Amino acid sequence: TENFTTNLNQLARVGGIDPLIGREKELERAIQVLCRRRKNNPLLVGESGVGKTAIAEGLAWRIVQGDVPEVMADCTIYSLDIGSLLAGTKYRGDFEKRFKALLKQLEQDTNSILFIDEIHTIIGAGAASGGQVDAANLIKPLLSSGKIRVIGSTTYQEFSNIFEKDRALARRFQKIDITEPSIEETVQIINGLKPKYEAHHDVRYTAKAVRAAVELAVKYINDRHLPDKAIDVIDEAGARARLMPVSKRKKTVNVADIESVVARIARIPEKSVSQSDRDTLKNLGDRLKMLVFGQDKAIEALTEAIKMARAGLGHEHKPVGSFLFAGPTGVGKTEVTVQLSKALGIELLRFDMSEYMERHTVSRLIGAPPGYVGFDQGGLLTDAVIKHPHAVLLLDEIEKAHPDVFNILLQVMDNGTLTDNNGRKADFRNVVLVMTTNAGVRETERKSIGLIHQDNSTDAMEEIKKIFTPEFRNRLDNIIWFDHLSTDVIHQVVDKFIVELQVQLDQKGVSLEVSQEARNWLAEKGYDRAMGARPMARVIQDNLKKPLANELLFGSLVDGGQVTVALDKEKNELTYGFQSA
Amino acid sequence: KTNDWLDEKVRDALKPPS
Ligand SMILES: Nc1ncnc2c1ncn2[C@@H]1O[C@H](COP(=O)(O)OP(=O)(O)OP(O)(O)=S)[C@@H](O)[C@H]1O
Ligand SMILES: Nc1ncnc2c1ncn2[C@@H]1O[C@H](COP(=O)(O)OP(=O)(O)OP(O)(O)=S)[C@@H](O)[C@H]1O
Ligand SMILES: [Mg+2]
Ligand SMILES: [Mg+2]
């Protein structure tokens, strides 16, 4: 019994068990249930991280300390180590000798109680050929007799799926619900546990710091329950303060330190803005304008929304931004979104929405229901967001997607989280949701009847309203209608494409010089308001790339070439001069 | 009006007689 089980009462005397703070209803229920018959044995079914082990182990510490009833004052508590019992069960009858011997000691004393943590495991523990014995069966007669009382703890899922299956054990055991405590109750627990953590790390936590940990952790960390989640910040905060300075100049834990620790655990960019990061944020609009010309309203909306999140003036349970980009073909809707990720140095979660045209395909985003071939792979959207909490979610061609797709996004915009088939929740608070749409684009290129063409921008918005539900538009932070590229804007676009060509030529050792007159000629030939910037690329391909390709493959530009481009005013045709150099 | 159609072995341990 020395190795099979451990004496929790003795452990508390040496300080092994941590101090028990709170949970007075659970302790009261456990003690009263133990003394009475008719399911004397209490159970501690609760969710993970809710302190189930602390209630059973904290009871032994309380009994040795005092302030317990006389009947329970002398009741010693032991914990069953299932691994120890099976360590030496090589030969037949070893388990019987160990389990029966242990039960005899507990039963004969009549005041010893065994606390079997994770009691779901003992239901089995043996399937060897011939024996046909189990730990639960060995103790089933004793529990039915009621001579021996045993405490237990199990997860809610395990109790319903494992403990509930064995009606005999479930019938005897008395369930005691355990749930996450209140915010006030949790900070009190940390104060009670503050001497232990402070001693190990040689740090001191301020009253505000413990309060901040509970509020900040619950706000940003959702998967874990409140007791362990809040304590995880305290333990990590002490370690960081202890380990960060080699000189040990800073021993106390400031509130600012708690914020930084919570940020890394929850992978949120929200923190005090750094000088290096601050500079980049200021020039985000300027850099975006250099790459994407025009569409200033779109850039302003993205930059201002992102700035608010770092400043802290952001939606509590919604994404930083939910922008719908609708415009004519060829305008830089996708480019600004793609370039935004590069400028901000964050991953681009580009999800083409043409593939999700069918209703059944939407399950792919949130995962296939359990029990199918594709359940294991999981959702593509939730997994991507979990892997990259701070990222740009570019849902291009959202119009093509099935109406069911929009339903999923409605929850993300307001609730701020989406649950997959597995049940994990993805945090979209730091995700920049930009959905490009081509709705009402035919009207944009439609030429109205009459001498003077009419502005069909209003007609396009009506089509967008028809395709998108009113509730969907209300949730969106802003709807930006991209304007048609002007002649001045197109001139900048031509230069940008030439720069891309120059970079490609640099790889081959060729340098391209385009005169100002040549650039104007290219712009006029390819400038179409309806088609957009894309025709400019086609003009560059035929006029510039095609001649260079022949020379590059077979000609003067094969190695270390040079190029000059000028516009023949008399012939109104470009002249390409190649020097072998 | 299209319709979409949606679509034992364990190791054991031996104990020698004591
Ligand atoms: N009411 C409480 N009073 C004091 N300390 C607590 C309390 N609840 C939790 N703690 C502390 O926080 C820890 C939480 O983890 P445990 O209680 O050990 O986990 P557990 O209940 O065994 O976990 P599962 O997931 O349910 S098996 C405890 O061990 C204590 O250190
Ligand atoms: N406003 C712009 N400024 C600079 N380059 C642009 C601009 N708009 C388009 N381009 C160029 O066109 C390409 C980017 O096109 P995208 O923005 O991806 O098109 P899009 O908005 O997805 O198109 P549709 O027709 O609206 S689906 C790159 O070659 C860009 O350099
Ligand atoms: Mg436990
Ligand atoms: Mg697009």
Image: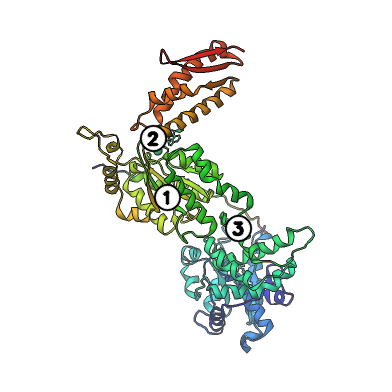
Residue at the left extreme, as displayed: A450
Disc 2 from disc 3: Cα separation: 40 Å
Camera-nearest label, 2 or 1: 2
Disc 2 from disc 1: Cα separation: 41 Å
| Location of ligand 1 given as a quarter of the image | bottom right
Is tag 3's residue or tag 1's residue first in the polypeptide sequence? 3
Q: Residue at x 44, y 42 (%)?
A: A351
Residue at the top extreme, as displayed: A555
Q: Find disc 1 in the rendering and name its residue.
A: A366
From the top left corner, tell me how far across and down residue A56 is, in percent: 60, 74
Q: Find disc 2 in the rendering and name its residue.
A: A486
Observer-nearest residue: A368 or A272?
A: A272
From the top left corner, tell me how far across and down residue A296 is, in percent: 44, 44
Place residue A215 in its image quadrant. Answer: bottom right
Q: Amino acid at mark 3?
A: Ser
Q: Callout 3: residue from which chain? A: A
Q: Is residue A14 left or right of residue A579?
A: right
Q: Determine whether the residue tagged by mark 2 lies in a helix, strand or loop.
A: loop
Residue A272, which numbered label?
Answer: 3
**What is the crowding at mark 3: few (fewer than 14 residues within 10 Å), some, or many (at least 20)?**
few
Q: Callout 1: residue from which chain? A: A
Q: Amino acid at mark 2?
A: Ser
| Residue A559 in view here | yes
Q: Determine whether the residue tagged by mark 1 lies in a helix, strand or loop.
A: helix
